[PDB]
Image (cartoon, one colour):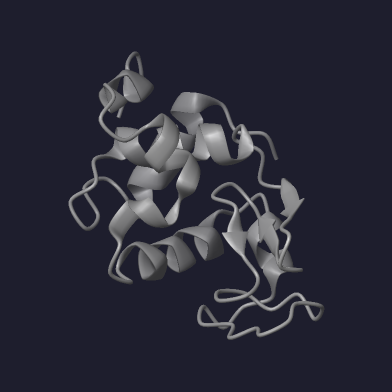
Length: 129
């Protein structure tokens, strides 16, 4: 599923990401935009043999099991395919763990490079939230 901007904002809010670990909703929408272009089905292979999955491009070395990744820990206890569903529940649950891991949203290099320090609330402008 390719979410609209406000559509994804509402879903993320509903699932408790607005201000989660102190990161406002705009931060999460901005991260999604640059990670996946709001596409749940996005995948990208990494040099180490892991792959990133879903709207928040969650990686298969630490977080989810894809059966092909060296050194996998599956800390979210989920198949990586669950992160490609139209239902963002699994991605959100796994993103809550990730952002709690010590480095906050810096765990998303696209967030650090493209969202951090910017006017992230622009990403929820116009939405009825």
